[PDB]
Image (cartoon, rainbow, N blue to C red):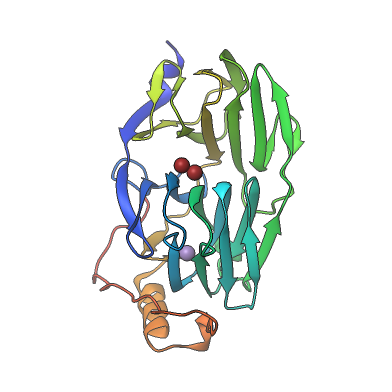
Length: 299
Ligand SMILES: [Br-]
Ligand SMILES: [Br-]
Ligand SMILES: [Mn+2]
């Protein structure tokens, strides 16, 4: 009853990435742009496809953010303009810090037939937004199990278990899977806002149903929340301290002013060293859409 005044639920939409691969896009949406520093969230799969038809995202840039890939099922090859080459497998995280700028590709091996993943972006704080880019791979995320749930701490600290993933603002991300039918209350930090998304199956958060077509978000203020999860179903919990500074998110860029975006777009179109090259990629380099002359910030 008390918790429900801090809860909002809204549908999430289908969208295409790479060469027509259909995914679900949860953030940004018309009702919610950010949860802590989390400023983008795609749910990919679960899906099975013919070998050779997996995700193929060609060269494209990012600025002012970190991309965060949580691979649940299947594999993906990450390549970037720093020369990183990393195959990500189930139960692993890739963290690419774009900062001042980087470009990358994400391509499924030609023998791969499955894909289940959550792809997020993290807005860098003002003091780190232009840092040198880097790429980090995490093959082992810690697991804490209680109340019939197996919690994998992806980032931050949850149930006194801290992920090795290094981020620059107060943030948390946890994958939860039920080992048995359960209903329990899980702890929350009152200074954080949160989002819940069903990764596999359905669940309930304070009585609100989580499906593959919605998301439940919480305002700051709660110390705990009740969830219901049948055995085998999986949920993603993300959260963080409200990001105070207004940001501009357009295409693959997170910035602060229109001039930042104009500059970066021009540099991409002109093959500027800022974004480097990915010489081993076979195919088309992705193109920047038109940049509107005016756009609203995150707040
Ligand atoms: Br799958
Ligand atoms: Br599947
Ligand atoms: Mn990307």
